[PDB]
Amino acid sequence: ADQLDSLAALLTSRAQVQLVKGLKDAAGLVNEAREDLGDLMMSFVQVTALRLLIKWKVFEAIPLEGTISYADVAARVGIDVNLITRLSWVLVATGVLKQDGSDKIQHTARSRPYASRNPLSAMMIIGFDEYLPALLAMPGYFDTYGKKEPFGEKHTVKAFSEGNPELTVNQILASSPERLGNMTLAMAAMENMYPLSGVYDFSWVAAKAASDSNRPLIVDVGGAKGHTLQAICKDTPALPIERCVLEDLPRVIQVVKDTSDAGAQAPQLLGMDFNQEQPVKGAVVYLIRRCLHDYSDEQCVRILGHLAAAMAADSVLLIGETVLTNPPSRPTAMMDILLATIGGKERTIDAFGAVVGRAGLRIKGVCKQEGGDFSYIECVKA
Ligand SMILES: Nc1ncnc2c1ncn2[C@@H]1O[C@H](CSCC[C@H](N)C(=O)O)[C@@H](O)[C@H]1O
């Protein structure tokens, strides 16, 4: 253990993706269970103070620069100064806020984002509002439904924790557009996970584009608003977006059309259900990015099967997903459990290989993002 202690010690000497990972592992080593439990409990109180002070517009009342008294803050937001102080003190002690003197509060780099509506503060809100209750409900959920991996769009941990297990997550939300708004803004933060253009080379697709002037190039299966297609084609004249196909449910496709500027360059648009047969045959590339992790292996096999039958011998299927290492990293282990609250999971390359093989495909290679585990798994017909 004395080496990591030294590794981090030389890291902190220069200080005066893993710059701070070793600081997590060092903390783990030295702490005993009772220090772990107090740290965990402090996390829950810290997030609660964060959520309330965002909700009550306190961070907004605190100037980005300079100092303001607790009294003045409380008068601005119209709230009991004692309650404002007690919750601020949680953030002072953890270093999210900074106290000057006995009575004065101020922002830090770590708290300024919470002073406005933005993807970070949106993520804070949905985490507290849309995932924490599901995690807290997990002991009762697994007593109620059986201690097995949760899948299916009804009776999610999330719907259970909200008191209506018969609703889907989307039905639950379409009843309150405010929750809708927070969720959509929050997902913008990682709307650009690492992109194909760069991480994957489509030069060979241009050669296919010339050799067959007639065939579909890239089909983005469940591609939402088609940001990934736009990025791939943007400045490649041999990769024409007009030869590509954006597929998603009819409701989201309709929104794509209703929110697109006239005369803009667009892929073909096709409303469809990727649990049923794939309408576009023989394309060069089928891309399914961040979709399979919402589903059981069995549903993933059905989805991939439709793609395999539509694919030609020289077609490739690109699966854009996190590929867990065995054991997984902290943030991907974390997401793995969050996905369980909504009926999904992350997977190792072995688990993907089992699902891919069952769909009559085989994994030809994997391109992994630098400094993370998000990958494109390149598959071809078996
Ligand atoms: N049955 C279905 N058929 C087609 N699309 C579906 C679907 N069920 C969910 N989706 C779509 O799958 C997407 C999952 S989110 C992933 C979006 C995009 N690939 C990205 O990289 O961010 C959503 O756009 C959703 O509309």
Image (cartoon, rainbow, N blue to C red):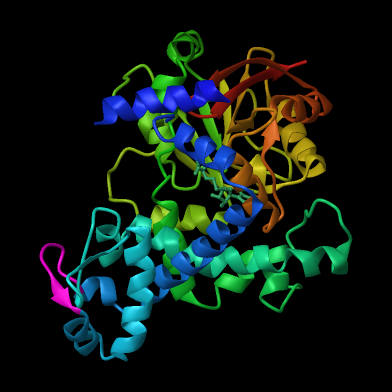
- Residue, x 42% and y 28% (percent of image)? 8
Locate the N terminus and report the quarter of the image it occupies. Answer: top right
Q: Is residue 64 magenta?
A: yes
Locate the C terminus and report the quarter of the image it occupies. Answer: top right
Q: Relative to 102, is 329 above or below?
A: above
- Residue, x 72% and y 54% (percent of image)? 343
Place of residue 50 in the rendered image (x, y in percent of width and height, measured from the top left): 39, 68
Q: Relative to 50, is 321 above or below?
A: above
Instruction: Indicate left or right for 4 with 71 as reference.
Output: right
Place of residue 165 in the rendered image (x, y in percent of width and height, measured from the top left): 75, 72
Place of residue 273 in the rendered image (x, y in percent of width and height, measured from the top left): 66, 48
Q: As rendered, which of 15 and 244 lies closer to the eye?
A: 15
Place of residue 146 in the rendered image (x, y in percent of width and height, measured from the top left): 89, 61
- Residue, x 43% and y 61% (percent of image)? 124
Which secondary structure is most common in the magenta stretch?
loop
Q: As rendered, which of 382 and 85 lies closer to the eye?
A: 85
Q: What stretch is highlighted in magenta?
A: 62-69
Let me know if residue 140 appears in the view.
Answer: yes
Instruction: Indicate left or right for 73 with 313 as reference.
Output: left
